[PDB]
Amino acid sequence: MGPAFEFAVAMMKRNSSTVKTEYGEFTMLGIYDRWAVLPRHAKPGPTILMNDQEVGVLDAKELVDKDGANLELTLLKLNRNEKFRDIRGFLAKEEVEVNEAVLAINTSKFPNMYIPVGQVTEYGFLNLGGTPTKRMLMYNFPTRAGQCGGVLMSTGKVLGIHVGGNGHQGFSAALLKHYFN
Amino acid sequence: MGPAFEFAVAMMKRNSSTVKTEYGEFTMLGIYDRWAVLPRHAKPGPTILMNDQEVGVLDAKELVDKDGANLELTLLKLNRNEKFRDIRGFLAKEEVEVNEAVLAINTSKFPNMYIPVGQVTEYGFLNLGGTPTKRMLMYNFPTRAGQCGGVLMSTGKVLGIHVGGNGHQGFSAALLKHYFN
Image (cartoon, rainbow over all chains, first blue to last red):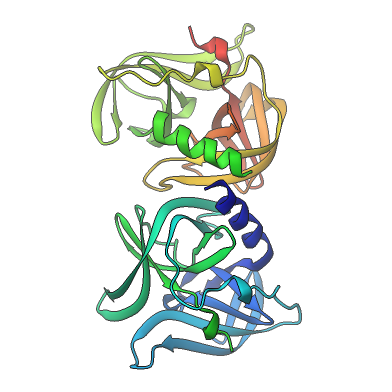
């Protein structure tokens, strides 16, 4: 658990920011270059607020699988000079299962908070409030709203982005390496 | 940092509970026997809610120093059979300063959350919203309300209880071993 928290703290400090869209405040992870990811429900507009400063959004991809199914992630390309530390080598080729994960949240409502969720299992398919969603990861933790965007991590691995919950279970979209080109 | 989080997680799981008084929801730490501590502002009544079950409060001591100054902690003795794991040997004789601390919160608004606050320094005297307060510990973290009661920890040490903040600084009351007799 300790090494996962140590990994998470350094990761969040280096690659995470707090983002405000018209739909709420979210944790955001920069992946490489000027590309980041948000949970789909952040519905970013043509501009976002990133650490309280206004930033233009050049592109927004709502990710779906080959048979069109919802993946619940939105990739965005930001209009800014500074480049994200490349973290693509932390992203698995496929769904990671682990016995000890930490979920990191970085917003106003949850500033630098970390949650031990323990075991993460590829749950896979999920009807996420009406929408057929795939590549879900599940862990047991008493969900609240505003955790959306939280980053799911273990030692050396960024596993996914928190996208939903039901009182004792949380769901992350798996953050796969191939999303990133 | 990792060992502190590992310490905190096990400590919270063993000795902490979520408590509702008429003044709010708070993290509570059981110390030994049927004695626990709350931040003063929890103002517990003759009964509390502890993990959603009603519990009688046999005694409540608002702690002050020898010259009467506010210490911002309330000790309470609970009317229940189950005994707290004795954690008095984790409590320092005097104010602990450390370079890496973790603040643990366990309520509905913040369920099993952990925050790296880094360096804790005996700040000592503080005018805590009108009240002259002593034996304060200070750390830098972007405070929100509902963190009251949070438990401040490092590897092997329970340092204090979170009692106040101002946007970038948090304050804990030092949890001294001698309070406990």
